Amino acid sequence: EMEKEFEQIDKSGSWAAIYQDIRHEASDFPSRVAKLPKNKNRNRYRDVSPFDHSRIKLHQEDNDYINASLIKMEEAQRSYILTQGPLPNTVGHFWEMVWEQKSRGVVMLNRVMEKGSLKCAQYWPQKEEKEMIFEDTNLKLTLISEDIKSYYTVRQLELENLTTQETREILHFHYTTWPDFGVPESPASFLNFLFKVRESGSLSPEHGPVVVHCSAGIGRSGTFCLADTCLLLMDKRKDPSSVDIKKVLLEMRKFRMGLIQTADQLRFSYLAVIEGAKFIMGDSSVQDQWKELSHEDL
Image (cartoon, rainbow, N blue to C red; front, side, top):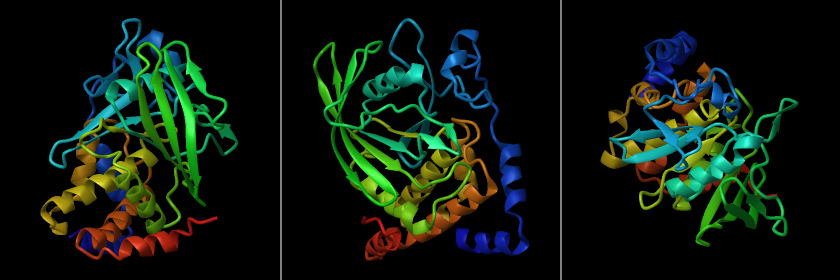
């Protein structure tokens, strides 16, 4: 039982030790393509790279490299693409990836400016009438509508392959109050957001993997995917006790380094999963309680 483990860790005050255990046990796979000289300006952080074996390849012949990883959760039957916040020179690559991987949703967990610094390029249009054209990858992106809540915004975007004139609807889910190296304000606000993503169909198997990012695509991004996968696993057999959060996180870290960047993000992950279990185990009313507690209106 995660809940009993939680209290044990809390009482002994050992979150930092548990977290360091995870760091020491985590997989170490090569990331040679990320470290090629020609890719230096495609990485935002020198010490965050995709492993070679799980990296997403762009379907282009010039340079197929993007700092993005496929996190394929076999037992849960859900995949995610985790990526860094795109750079000015990789915004075209970013949308190329979305197109090629057939994703329906993009989950953004950071602000463009955080702690006085630019953490992400402004990679989507903010006004309907000012669409973006990415000339390197032959794609056009138009804002269709937006739904602004108090701590997150949902945007409907239209992505068009200019070569073929096919179009796709992309949903952009922007969490705007989640601090860098920090945690959401509450389990309720995070779970309300996660369920909003789930209820859009973006995580569904008929679509490509959802794209999840923050600035580096490991800390906040890891917390989002860890909670989702743990809840899905529980949903499968209706058996909360069958889920070992730490082992799930280590599996995920087989596909991208560094997932969950602080011991407090780990602790938040437990809280979110424990609370989300109420819904999975049949108390549907808790969804509405989270909406109210999140104070999303205005």
